[PDB]
Image 1 (spheres, rainbow, N blue to C red):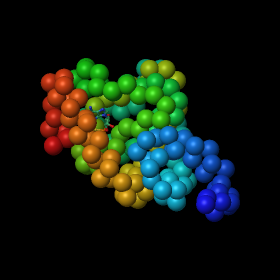
Image 2: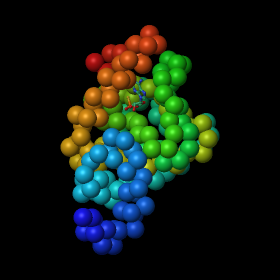
Image 3: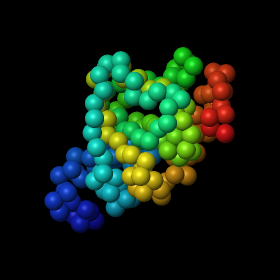
Length: 153
Ligand SMILES: Nc1nc(Cl)nc2c1ncn2[C@@H]1O[C@@H]2CO[P@](=O)(S)O[C@H]2[C@H]1O
């Protein structure tokens, strides 16, 4: 039972965040304690229509979850993924310690929650492997479209 995870001061933030984390597919699968710790450390920010969230080729230190809005990822001007509420992105640079492999732009008013590298390494350590084999699905799209894949391998 979870009464223990929602009793203290931190409980308000813990609770708005938990329904949300419950629909981010790869972390909906973390168990509750681990997921409550993520909720504790999330921060919020917003992007306007047209703003760049991630610029391809830059160093990246931030992991994102989209909680509202529409954003789109492209690489060498090819659309490789559309994002909506519940999606996460920006993990690959944190896992591989390489520059951002793609650009992500807001397509309307977007609200996100995020973790920095130290928080991502600390809290999401238990699942770096599961996150990592999602990357194979990234290869397919890179290949589907004839784009460079050395950013992954
Ligand atoms: N087909 C895809 N290939 C790749 Cl390498 N990254 C993809 C793909 N689709 C989305 N992304 C995401 O765009 C982000 C760009 O900053 P990262 O740290 S490299 O993380 C990246 C991924 O989360």
